[PDB]
Picture (cartoon, rainbow over the protein chains, first blue to last red):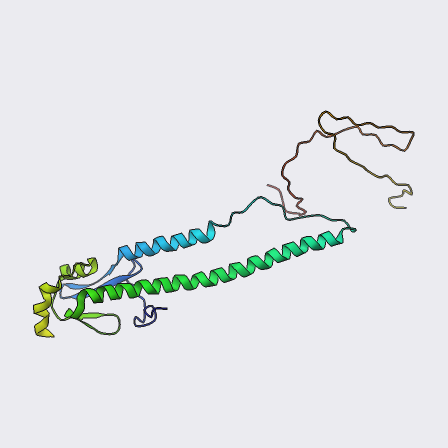
Amino acid sequence: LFGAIAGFIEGGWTGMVDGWYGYHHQNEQGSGYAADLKSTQNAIDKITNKVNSVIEKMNTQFTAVGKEFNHLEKRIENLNKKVDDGFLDIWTYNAELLVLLENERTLDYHDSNVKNLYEKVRNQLKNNAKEIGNGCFEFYHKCDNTCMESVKNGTYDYPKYSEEAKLNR
Amino acid sequence: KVRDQEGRMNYYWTLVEPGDKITFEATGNLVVPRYAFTMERDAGSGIIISDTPVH
């Protein structure tokens, strides 16, 4: 558990519908949502792979579990029942535990993705911005839509805005 | 007496291999075959006992 989903970010965004993890920017040119498509696609691929691994690893074979025994073959009927009950117990325990564990894995996987996005942005801005605490960054320098498109992309030019940010810090 | 009869009839079956022969010899009490079944088998399945309709 990393502490982002239901942590220092206390809620999801219903408005942001074009992805799973994203940004919300507020400039003098306006406000908007913009999902991070690369991280969302990576998450989709990995969750898809997990679903495929759980579903497409069964390797079932043709069988007929029903067997008929007469009144004088009660012991063999009991053996067949025992086999069936043992298989049922093994499979129910394994299925329940597997689902319970992989649900944890998926939820912590998403929580790690959100944290990683936050740390990437934070390390990319350094001291040009102030960390509010809710999960947000208030810029010390006035920067436009191109600046935040660069921050989303990962090409923030810190030296460009450093001198501007020093005066207001 | 079950089904109005006090005697009995035991029913027997066998599989004759290709090229093999079956021989019946009797002085009485024999219910001879009339129809045999040329049969070819597979891996095996079961018998579903149900009232569900067949479609």
